[PDB]
Image (cartoon, coloured by chain):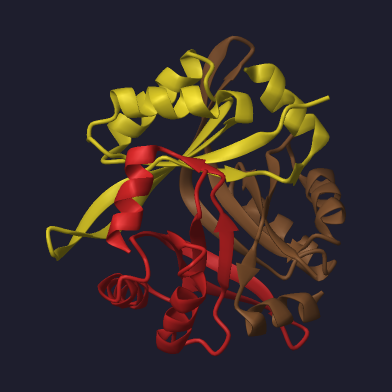
Chain colours: A red, B yellow, C brown
């Protein structure tokens, strides 16, 4: 039904999530971005449980653009190994999908 | 045996509308559950410039057999012309939860 | 190994942090993002309920998914908590590498 995909990326703060989004959108590697602030991320680091504040990003693009988008985000992300995951979209409204493709 | 389940993404302009859209699709049994995350920000280009809106992220859970009708219903009552309507697959899940999800519809 | 994203909700911040802490300590997940301030609407026994919840998003591999859900369900206060798995078709290599290595 669609090659559109959603990319998950974790940002340390709103300002960072903000220009990462602005950046990829300007480059047209993403059609749109949703930012969900107020979260924390837990993970182990050197036998220690780390917790940090984060903003969950949800970007929309396609499989033909996924790699290019990931690299752009990677290059501008302050973290060394930021979370960059691609989730497949099995279906979507036709008008919304057309709008996303047109934006890319 | 359970029918394939999916997660639907949709965004509403405010909490009032989010709860309203959710309550309707749940009443019509087009979705088994809805999670609403307020305070989100939607960024996208429109007419050549970057737009930014405060929105509520909706995460609706239903089955592949209902997705179509769910999307149709959400779009029918949604405040704007072309709302976010994306369907993500659930390749695995707790059997009991998936059963409640299914029986719920 | 293919990785996946797991969605689970907790009735409160403490439960969410405790659930993430133990699955990570058990090395059944690489990381978990906790998002407070959410709401869950659903019908229960013919009634519309709206409960406060913290949205959890956990990252692990397809090899640990079954084990991760069992552990989360085991320690979760609810009898039948939301436990759903979504596939990841692609991802940054270094990140996917770390994710696997963390388990």
Q: Is residue B76 left or right of residue A72?
A: left
Q: Quadrant of residue C62?
A: bottom right
Q: Quadrant of the N terminus of chain B?
A: top right
- Please give the name of the residue rendered at 49% of the width and 52% of the height, measured from the top-left corner: C36
- Determine whether C1 is above or below B89 in the image: below
Point out residue B60 in the picture as x, y percentages from the top left corner. Answer: 51, 35
Q: Quadrant of residue C1?
A: bottom right
Point out residue C55 in the picture as x, y percentages from the top left corner. Answer: 56, 49
- Please give the name of the residue rendered at 55% of the width and 13% of the height, measured from the top-left corner: C47
Point out residue C78 in the picture as x, y percentages from the top left corner. Answer: 73, 35
Point out residue C20 in the picture as x, y percentages from the top left corner. Answer: 70, 60
Q: Nearer the viewer, residue B62 or A37?
A: B62
- Determine whether C43 is above or below A103 in the image: above
Q: Nearer the viewer, residue C82 or C85?
A: C85
**Residue A94: in sight, yes or no?**
yes
Q: Is residue B91 left or right of residue A94?
A: right
Q: Quadrant of the C terminus of chain B?
A: top right
**Residue B40: in sight, yes or no?**
no
């Amino acid at each position: 039904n669609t090659a559109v995909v959603v990319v998950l990326c974790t940002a340390p703060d709103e300002a960072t999530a903000q220009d990462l989004a602005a950046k990829v959108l300007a480059e047209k590697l993403a059609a749109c971005a949703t930012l969900i602030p107020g979260a924390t991320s837990l993970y182990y680091w050197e036998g220690k449980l780390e917790q940090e504040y984060v903003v969950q990003m949800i970007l929309k693009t396609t499989v033909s653009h996924q790699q290019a988008l990931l690299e752009c985000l990677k290059s501008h992300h302050p973290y060394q190994t930021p979370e960059l995951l691609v989730l497949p979209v099995t279906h979507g409204d036709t008008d919304y999908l057309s709008w996303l493709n047109a934006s890319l």
